[PDB]
Structures are given as structure tokens and as C-alpha cells.
Length: 433
Length: 99
Figure 1 (cartoon, helix red, strand yellow):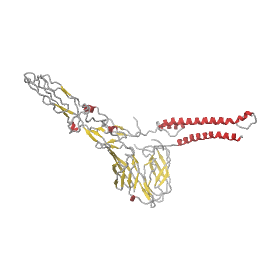
Figure 2 (cartoon, chains in turn green, orange):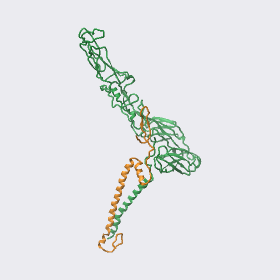
Figure 3 (tube, rainbow over the protein chains, first blue to last red):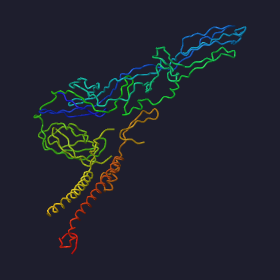
Figure 4 (cartoon, helix red, strand yellow):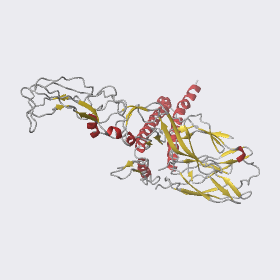
């Protein structure tokens, strides 16, 4: 047998519900989410990390000059330098005259943390959602099960042909352009992939680690070697993306609302418990039994001992009753106002016993079912002093329904007499003639 | 700091983050004297009480004053009959007097 439902998103809290059938004894369930897994169809786009800058041997002669070329490197420079006149220790100044020979050829390359550590710049696409649950139904114990959100998924565990949702709600806080270092992760508005951002963030403007395409600019500029010093004075840009690696902010996981978290590899969002889920599950109709063979109900009465409106099922109340014959029988809460600790109990002969429950009410007047026999225990006044309550408006009290009807009736009656007055007068005036 | 029973994140230092519902704070007696229940319908909710209070007092006052005007209307209408008596003739035993 298959029974379906729409359950609200309750990542932590369990969910029992008794399920019955004419001529058949009922059976309960217990569904309880274990995971929620929201996997976008993302991908990385390009990486970035610190650069490096090397210099080849700067040319030199006694006179004349060599020539600067396009030694292929990012931001690479080279320039002749004339009348160099540089000395070497214990030397002869490398000339007899104007040296004129100094190219100061340059080179820019990439750092080595890049291997260990580099940018992780992503485009994040639609992708999927899934989730894990636990079913402890009927006669079944903890059966934790995981499946995708899609309202189609045919999944059978034991006799449970799971069909899930899909969820009413349709969003997770993500973004197409989100980057990450280490455990942390950050929506970078856009990693300016092709566009060399002066190295300000695109310090390593490369598709991959192994993609040796540095469309970045350290703005390397050479200065004239001088002072008889063999060197390549120069300038270039500081590692701007590192400069931001001083200005890193709050990772999104730390900002994710609904007190829920994220998984690294799939960008699985983790249990932002929002929405409702139209689930559909097959049950073993064999697990049913008859309805007439059952120890039957009778002599229905329950005593509302006491509840104080608190989170824990902070209310105890009992029953007083006489049975057809002893045994066991479920006590479902079709109205989960006083959220019952219990869902199924033994029913001994004259089952006259208690139970526990929480409602946010100052007091209810409600009822629920037991052993295919819904009985009424209204719910006394409740003292005040993680988890839910009833809380909608069930906290109703005496004075509320007292004064509301007081004022309504007073106004109604007075205005009714008022309107009566007019025709009451007019009738005999008509009678005059 | 304060929060609903919704919990809230917190961690200073290597301390892991923890999150605890804030409750055990009812702060109001559902039924005492009418002034007491007034302070209750002030406090049972912090603000929803207050908005309910202001709107409810407004609407009840306007209802009562409308009733009052209709009362006065009906009363003068009830006055209107006896204007026969300007004839200055025999009495018909009503609440008002001319013996």
C-alpha cells in the first residue's frame, strides 16, 4: 500500500503519523531528516596566486651594445644602457671606454605556493538538491535514507517506495561567481578572468595552475643600472591579490542564514530547514491486520492533569477508562497542539493512564485520537517557564473569549435597538390617517 | 545580547561555535485583575501585544462613540412625538411631566 503526504521542512525534528485503513488496524511512521544536500552544477573557471620575477644575465662589453628582444615573459622588459662603466671587484671595470652594453633583460613568472595554494574561481550553475532522512515507522526502527529532491525519485527501502517532494521552496543562498581559499569561501563578484586587473586581484591571470597563460600585468618597469653596480634596478606591482589576502572578509558559510552550513566538494548546502516536501511512500499492506480482531475501545475519558507552556513536552495528562480486552493500540495526535511525547501505547484492560505533551497554549480545549477512537481532553491553564510548539493562536484564555463576546454583543444589541426606534415611532404615525 | 528561541551562533577564539535558544522568559500573568491582564496583553508578546492594544482601543472607542451618536439620534426621534402637546390639551401619562 502507498500513502503520500507533504511534509514541512523539519531538518532535525522527527515525524510520526498513524496510518489506518477500513477493516485494517493502523500503523504509525517516524520520518526524520538526516541531511539536506543542495548541489549546484558549478565549476571553476580560472586560478590566481602570487607571481615571481627573475632576471637573466644583463649584457656587458668594453664598448658598443647588444640588443633587447622580446624574451617572452609576462610584463617582461629590456632596455639598452649606454656608458655603463661598471666595476667588478679586483677587476678592470670590464671596459677601456664607454661600455654602452647593458640590456637589463627581465622576466616575470609565477610563485610556488600556486601549487599548494592558488585561487579557486568558479561559475556556479543550477545543479540539484538532495537530503537524508530517517524512517522509523510502524514496526520499523531507525532506517536512515537519503535521496534527491525531485518529485519523481523512485526509491525502495524495505517496503518503503520513497518518492520525495520536490520541495515547495526553491532557493539556496549561492552565486555563480564565488571563490574559495582553504576551508573558507567567498562570493567574488566576478574574478576578472581574461582582464588583467593590474594584478590587483588578477595577480596570476591564468586559466589553471598548469595553464601558463599570464594575462596579468605586474607593470614591471626597469630602472637604469648605475653606480658601477651590475644590477637591474626596476619596478613592478606588489602582489595585489595578496594585498587583498590582507583584506579577506567573512566567508559565506559564516553568513549563511537559517543557521545552516555548506559542504566543500559539491557546494552542498546543509539543512536550511525551509519549505514543505510532498513525499510519497509505499507501505507494506501485508503489515496491516484486521480491525475486528482488535481489543476494542470503550469507556472513553481522559483527565487533563496539567501542562505548562514550555519547549519540552512539558505537560502531563492521563485517562480513565475501561477496555473491551487488554493489549496495545496507537494514540495518534491528529491535532498536535499539545505535542504529545507519545504516539502509541499499550492498552491494558481499563487502560487508564497518562502521557506527556507540550503546547504553547495558555490553555487549549482540543482533542486527538487513540486506538481509532478520538477522545477529548481539553487542556488546562498552563504556566510559563530548540524546538517547536503549537503557538499559532491556541494560547487562548478565558478573558479573551469573555471580553470579545462582551463588547461585540453590547455594540450589536445597542445598535439594533437604535435602528428599531425609527420604524417603531413611524408605524403609528402612519396609523394616524 | 538577546534572541528568540531560534538560537544564535557565537564563538570567540578557538572556541567552536555554539547556538542556544533563548527562553525561560514568560514575563506576564495571563489572568489577574483587569489592570493585571492589561499589563499581560501588554507583555505576553512584547510588541504584538502593543499593536493589538493600540488598534483594539481605537476600534472599541470608535464603536462606542458611534453607538452613542445613534443613541442621541434615536432619543431626539423619541422626543419628536409629544409635539402634539403644543395643542396644550389632555395628558397621556408618560415619563415626562406636566401635572
